[PDB]
Length: 96
Length: 96
Image 1 (cartoon, rainbow over the protein chains, first blue to last red):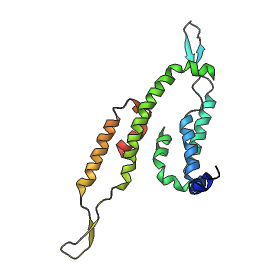
Image 2 (image 1 turned 90 degrees about the vertical axis):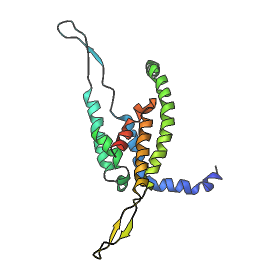
Image 3 (image 1 turned 180 degrees about the vertical axis):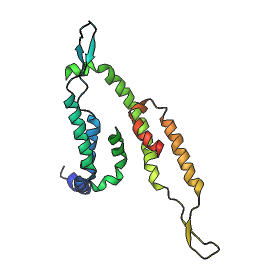
Image 4 (image 1 turned 120 degrees about the horizontal axis):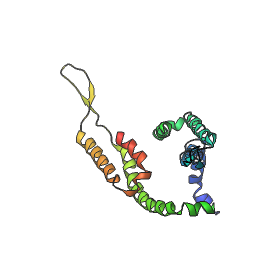
C-alpha cells in the first residue's frame, strides 16, 4: 500500500541491504537443514534363492549427491564475513 | 501428493501435537537465548606490593548463578514432549 511503502521504508531498505549477507545465507541454510538428504532411502522388496523376503535399497547417487551439495554449500557459507555469528550451527551440520 | 498426505496422516496429526509443545517451549528458550550475551565479567584495577598494575575480577556469584539458572532451565526444557525436534540446540548450550 502507498502509505505503507513510505511508513515502512526503513524496515524494507535494511532488509534489502542485508540481502548481500546474513539473510540470503539464512534462507539457503534453512533449506539445506530442512532437506537434509536428497530422498528417503528407497524400500524395495527383494527375494533371494531360498525363499526369504527382504526390503532393499536403490538409487544411492540421488542421496549422496545431495550430501555433497550440502557440504560444498557449507564451504560456500564458510567464506561469508558474517560466519562468526553463525559458526555454531555450521558445526552441527558439519558433523551430521 | 494426495497419496502421500493420506499415507502419512498418522504422523501429521502427531506432528501438529508436537508443534504445539515445541512452539511453547521454543518461545521460552528464545528468552534464554536472548539472555546470554549481556553478562559482563567484572573488570577492576588492582595494585600489588611491588608497584605493578593489573585488572582483576569481582562479583562472581552474579555470573555463576545465571549459569545455574540456565542449566536448570535446560533441564526444564528436557521435560517437554516437543524436545525431540529441538534436542540439537540443547546439546550446544549443554556443552557450552
